[PDB]
Picture (cartoon, rainbow, N blue to C red):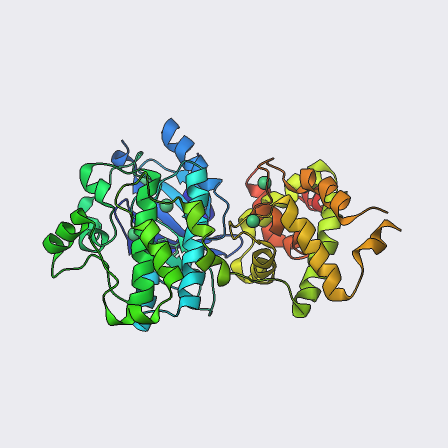
Length: 414
Ligand SMILES: Nc1ncnc2c1ncn2[C@@H]1O[C@H](COP(=O)(O)O)[C@@H](O)[C@H]1O
Ligand SMILES: [Ca+2]
Ligand SMILES: [Ca+2]
Ligand SMILES: [Cl-]
Ligand SMILES: [Mg+2]
Ligand SMILES: [Mg+2]
């Protein structure tokens, strides 16, 4: 475990939910701010708790809440995560009341990418709804972040503190029968998508009694007038997600790959991205030239101590390279991105041999950037190798890296 009070100062409260309370805290050395969920230990239901929390920490996906550490004192567990300032997707729906097909697809693609990644890691959300999706900031096209999952097996929730009425719109019919498989998240995501495009829940009613009665029948329609102005492709995706029988309901990956999603997720590099692509390429080569000790040390600092404001350019590059929208870079995506980079420069990729091809270059690189051997370059691995090492050289950040384990320490990093 570890000592929370030594490392962090509590600044203010941010919210209260089912499992505990969420506060803003500040790292005493770096002054970097974080969100911390504080859970009373008597609420447990600590060895297996830390084991399941460890899996949560290693989730590394741009649309999933990022957790940095779990600390403990005599009364509480502290789960310290990235701080998001844009509020709940719920509030954005209220303000806009509904979204263009282009805007809805961009939002729901991120939900699909996050849920796919969760399911591949054997995690079911079980309460997916707009109140549990935060915007990372107030910036226009910012990433959304799925929150509020993973603790239901280890800790006792207070049913009162959860917004039951809100949840009811979103629950799959099999949940009313005691079932919580992966497919229930797909149904909830389909309710979200229905709402993004129409502004209205597909299963609706005055109060919770009428809503749940409609959920149990599974019956919904595209009868509202605004559905006449919405494409058949979007309706086809919704019909596949809101299938009554979970066995016939499509998977999250099939959601992510649906043609309607692909049409509006064509982000690809352009001439204006060349400065940052060139920046990323130089830093990656330097990273791939440093020894296994330096590399693992750099990954640790980039993934835990960098800020959203410092990774924003690299996050846009990552998204443009991520052709299949799953929030990870596979071998072919790096090869294609390399080819696109050269094309944008006006350079024939065959000039490289005069001393190997893009394909040989990437295949030699994959074992060095995929430090965890996952088969793909996750977000934190890309940032660590592509970030300018200069920003990681902050004295405060070195101080924090040291304290987690000095004059010699600083030189070794340098
Ligand atoms: N990472 C975060 N950044 C900012 N606010 C958060 C974060 N996590 C939770 N919150 C706030 O705390 C509330 C309850 O959190 P939760 O119990 O995880 O649903 C959320 O609805 C947000 O208002
Ligand atoms: Ca990908
Ligand atoms: Ca990996
Ligand atoms: Cl949490
Ligand atoms: Mg205490
Ligand atoms: Mg919540």
